[PDB]
RNA sequence: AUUUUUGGUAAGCAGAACUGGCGAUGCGGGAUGAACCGAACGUAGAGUUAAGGUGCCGGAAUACACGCUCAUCAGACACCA
RNA sequence: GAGUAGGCAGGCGUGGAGGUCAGUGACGAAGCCUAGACCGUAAGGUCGGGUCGAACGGCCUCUAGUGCAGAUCUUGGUGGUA
RNA sequence: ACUUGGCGGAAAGGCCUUGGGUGCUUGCUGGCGAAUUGCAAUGUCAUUUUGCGUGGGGAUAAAUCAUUUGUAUACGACUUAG
């Protein structure tokens, strides 16, 4: 059947969709998509 | 009395054996083992070597020596149940093997006599070999079973 | 006296409580929750499970009892808060810790090395059932006894050699590979 | 000297259902049931004692050593196996005191009689 | 150079069995490249060994060896019967054995 | 002989292949079957459809889950027919079936590996010319299997790329055969033709 | 239970004749089965066979030879379904 | 060289009894525990280790309230359900 | 061991393909060495799961309970919030 080859996100995900990935959110350092956002450091090489 | 007493104790005098009717006869070596034949060794330190057959001993073993300057195999005993006689034979009408007996290989580094008399037989053997083409390179090379090779189908 | 231990009596103190009127099954389970801990983490844990913050995981005597979230800590689904058991073992932790201080053991490395709950003789009452029958109504008291020892690392280091036996063929091949 | 000792059935003849029940001991007892699979000898059940298993008469009562075991109480009893050293092995009785074992082992080696027990009782 | 082989590749098929009952004394061995009992009769009386690796060094090496010899042929299709000094353990049904060219001819 | 055999399951009788493979696995020979969707069964499409529908209707009444699972894929139809011919309940059988893999088409690593056949389980070698047969590609989909033409796409891609590979290998083997033919009439070549090689 | 045989539509029913079996009997085979087939049994080794089989499960020829059969309800080993 | 019901024979084990081994034993009897050992086709016997603390055994014979898994057995104790 | 351009997504985790370097070469003649593993004893050379100290690169969190909600709730669980 169908299988997910890969997913790519935009560098700027709102605090709305960031809150999704945590169950004890306000204790967290909110480090979700920090390294993934830093993959847009150059002209989005990892993204392209 | 922890135990009463057995009244009859066996005669602990040991009896003599019956006179065995079987005297040792001289071995019937298979026709394929003729002094001068190249034997593939099957076991021991020198397993899968090619060796040259020189003499039948009193112990029903084979005095052989793949000349030390071809395959590093000295003058050695080898059992005939651990050799494959090849159909290739070197002339052995110029070697004095009459020196070697069973007490020669009494075990009781290497002895100087044993090294020099190795060199004496080796000189005669390598003189006979170098006549025939590729036979030193054959004797140099070791034996191994390959893929597709069926021992029962393989002639020697 | 004091069931099988593999620790040093020079570095141990013990405490015994015979014929203590507690549910044997509850007090076996508080003892197996506390076993192999530091005495400080153990004492603190028993006050937490009295005021319903963490629970005693019931592992063996865990039949038709309600599930609870406070079990997830221990990788179980079913846990409880045996007040009476917890209070009796607390009394025996404290009494052991007092003997361990009176002998002179550093109260910091003191960790419960052995804890065992046996069954006491059952106490006899009679209930009254329908159609004028009598039944037994038995308490199952407990024999609690625990040991607390000082923690020591640097062990084994053990044990034996490679006292090897070889044949002429083995030793000859060793002498060959050396010559190579 | 002796022929190479064989024992046709080495492992013990445990009573049927001795494993199953504690009331039942493994001390061999013949199954005298009307439907017993052990008595009727079905393919897969335990083997029963049969005279056919009987050990060779030349190897019977010999230990691995090759000596018929003789229980010995005191030196008086040991001094009977004097002309029978190739034949027997003295074995001190279970109820003999340590000091009496000192005397027997002294006398046993002095005559040259093999012993299986002490040990010297340390 | 690559090859070092001085045995034939045998495989432990099964024991000598009925439709149901098995005889663990006679082990059935399939030899590589044999077809009939006639082809198999070369290997009658040869020395088969089962080489396996334990985790404990016993007397120099962690490898141990269970020795046997070919007794006779089996069936129509070149299988042989082997007897081993100690019987094989049966977990080796499909494990390779080594058919040496010992007692030679 | 090989460490792992690879069998092209095309133009093969299901049960005959299954018996051959079942004995290989118990003897302890690692085998993968590929192109399991071109297997064949004796008798017309309809007979084997009805045989399957007779198998489908067999379910555990009191809970149709725990009942006999009816696997629809041609790879899993073969596996059923092969697991029938092994004592799968025993540890030897579990270990024997562990040596087997079955695929609908020729995936990776096996896409560039050599593919054998088993002449005693070929339709062409066995069935009388005139008798009608099934294709597990059509049967499997008529009974539930969804991926008929996903496998037809992936096979059509693999066969284009493998046709390019062969056309290059053959074009080369012309140069190797030509140079080996121009090595004849040499001292060495006459000595080899004497020894037979 | 084969054969002879009475009653009975009949029966894994009732009742007889001769013999052989189970009962009181394990073992190899008929998948399984008291009775069918083969063979009756101390403990082992080796060899050879019985009935029955030798695609795979499953030890053993996907043996050889002459024919027949294509079934959208094939057929497949006596007692026996 | 099979075997139910059954018969007979040869033994194994227990409480006592007469005789004997000038038997063993507080430097440890008997009892109990023992993924230690040896003997016996077996019933069983013997030994090592532990616990324990006051008696007990081999052999030739006499005698019997003499050998247990079943009796919805008896008494006492114990469980799983929980 | 390193570079060149590429090609592979069905499980592509692999296929090619450059130039270079550094080793070997039994294509062919040479020159030494090998014994004593004693007449066989697998006579040990493969592929994993590895924590263990070394010395270099790199990054610097979450979940659970307790509290809270009611889109959920027998108890767990689920959804919320801090």
Image (tube, coloured by chain):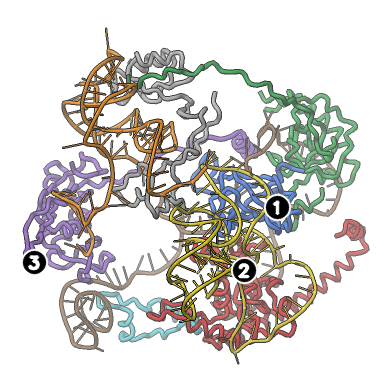
Chain colours: A cyan, B green, C purple, E blue, F red, G yellow, H orange, I brown
Please say if G21 is above or below A36. Answer: above
> Label 2 to label 3, Cα distance in Å?
69 Å
Circles 2 and 3 on the same subunit: no
* Secondary structure of the residue carrying numbered label 1: loop
- Residue at image mark 3: C129
Please say if B93 is above or below C24. Answer: above
Tell me the subunit letter for badge 2: F
- Residue at image mark 2: F21
* Residue displayed at 78% across by 53% down: B153
Check disc 3: other Cα within 10 Å, few if <14, some if 14-19, many if 20+.
few
Q: Is C112 in front, or is F7?
A: F7
* Secondary structure of the residue carrying numbered label 2: helix
Please say if E104 is above or below F136. Answer: above
Q: Nearer the viewer, mark 1 or mark 2?
A: 2
Q: Position of residue C106 (x, y in %)?
A: 18, 46
- Residue at image mark 1: E3
């Amino acid at each position: 059947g169908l299988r997910s080859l890969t997913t790519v996100w935009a560098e700027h995900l709102s605090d709305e969709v960031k809150r999704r990935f945590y169950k004890n959110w306000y204790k967290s350092k909110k480090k979700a998509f920090t390294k993934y956002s830093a993959k847009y450091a150059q002209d989005g090489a990892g993204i392209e | 009395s922890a135990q009463k007493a057995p009244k009859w104790y066996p005669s602990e005098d040991v009896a003599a054996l019956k006179k065995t009717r079987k005297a040792a006869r001289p071995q019937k070596l298979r026709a394929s083992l003729v002094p001068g034949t190249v034997l593939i060794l099957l076991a021991g330190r020198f397993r899968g070597k090619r060796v040259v057959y020189l003499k039948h001993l009193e112990d029903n073993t084979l005095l052989i020596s793949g000349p030390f300057k071809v395959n590093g195999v000295p003058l050695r005993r080898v059992n005939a149940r651990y050799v494959i006689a090849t159909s290739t034979k070197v002339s052995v009408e110029g070697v004095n093997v009459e020196k070697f007996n069973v007490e020669y290989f009494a075990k009781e580094e290497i002895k100087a006599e044993r090294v020099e008399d190795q060199k004496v037989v080796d000189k005669a053997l390598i003189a006979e070999i170098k006549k025939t083409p590729l036979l030193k390179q054959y004797l140099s090379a070791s034996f191994s079973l390959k893929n597709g090779d069926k021992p029962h189908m393989l002639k020697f | 006296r004091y069931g099988a231990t593999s620790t040093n009596p020079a570095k141990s103190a013990s405490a015994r409580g015979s014929y203590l009127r507690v549910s044997f099954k509850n007090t076996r389970e508080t003892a197996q929750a506390i076993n192999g801990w530091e005495l400080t983490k153990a004492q603190k844990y028993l006050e937490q499970v009295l005021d319903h913050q963490r629970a005693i995981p019931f592992r063996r005597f865990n039949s038709s009892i309600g599930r609870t979230a406070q079990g997830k800590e221990f990788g179980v689904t079913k846990a409880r808060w045996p007040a009476k058991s917890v209070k009796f073992v607390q009394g025996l932790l404290q009494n052991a810790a007092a003997n361990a201080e009176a002998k002179g053991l550093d109260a910091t490395k003191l960790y419960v090395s052995h804890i065992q709950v046996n069954q006491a003789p059952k106490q006899r009452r009679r209930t009254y059932r329908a159609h004028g029958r009598i039944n037994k109504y038995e308490s199952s008291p407990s024999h609690i006894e625990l040991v607390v020892t000082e923690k020591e690392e640097a062990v084994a280091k053990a044990a034996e050699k490679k006292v090897v036996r070889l044949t002429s063929r083995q030793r000859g091949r060793i002498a060959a590979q050396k010559r190579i | 000297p002796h022929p190479k000792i064989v024992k046709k059935h080495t492992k013990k003849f445990k009573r049927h259902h001795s494993d199953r029940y504690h009331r039942v001991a493994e001390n061999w007892r013949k199954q005298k049931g009307i439907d017993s699979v052990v008595r009727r000898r079905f393919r897969g059940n335990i083997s029963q004692p049969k005279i056919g298993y009987g050990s060779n008469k030349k190897t019977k009562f010999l230990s691995p050593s090759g000596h018929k075991t003789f229980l010995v109480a005191n030196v008086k009893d040991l001094e009977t196996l004097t002309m029978h050293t190739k034949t027997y092995a003295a074995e001190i009785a279970h109820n003999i005191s340590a000091k009496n074992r000192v005397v027997i082992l002294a006398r046993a080696k002095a005559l040259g009689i093999k012993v299986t027990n002490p040990k010297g009782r340390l | 150079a690559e090859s070092h082989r001085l045995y034939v590749k045998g495989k432990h098929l099964s024991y000598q069995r009925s439709k149901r009952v098995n005889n663990p004394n006679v082990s059935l061995i399939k030899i590589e490249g044999v077809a009939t009992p006639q082809d198999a009769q070369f290997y009658l009386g040869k020395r088969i060994a089962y080489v396996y690796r334990a985790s404990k060094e016993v007397r120099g090496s962690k490898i141990r060896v269970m020795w046997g010899k070919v007794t006779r042929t089996h069936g129509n299709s070149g299988v042989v019967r082997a007897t081993f000094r100690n019987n094989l353990p049966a977990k080796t049904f499909g494990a390779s054995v080594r058919i040496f060219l010992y007692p030679s001819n | 002989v090989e460490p792992v055999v690879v069998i092209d399951g095309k133009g093969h009788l299901v049960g005959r292949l299954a018996s051959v493979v079942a004995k290989q696995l118990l003897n302890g020979q690692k085998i993968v079957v590929v192109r399991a969707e071109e297997l064949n069964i004796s008798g017309e499409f309809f007979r084997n459809k009805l045989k399957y529908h007779d198998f489908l209707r067999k379910a555990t009444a009191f809970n149709k889950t725990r009942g006999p699972f009816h696997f629809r894929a041609p790879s899993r139809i073969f596996y059923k027919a092969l697991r029938g011919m092994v004592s799968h309940k025993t540890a030897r059988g579990k270990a024997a079936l562990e040596r087997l893999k079955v695929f609908e088409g020729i995936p990776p690593p096996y896409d560039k590996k050599k593919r054998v056949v088993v002449p005693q389980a070929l339709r062409v070698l066995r069935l009388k010319p005139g008798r009608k047969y099934t294709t597990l590609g059509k049967l499997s989909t008529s009974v539930g299997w969804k991926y008929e033409d996903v496998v037809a796409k992936l096979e059509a891609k693999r066969k284009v790329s493998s046709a390019e590979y062969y056309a290059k290998k053959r074009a080369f083997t012309k140069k190797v055969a030509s140079a080996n033919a121009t090595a004849a009439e040499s001292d060495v070549a006459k000595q080899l033709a004497a020894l037979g090689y």
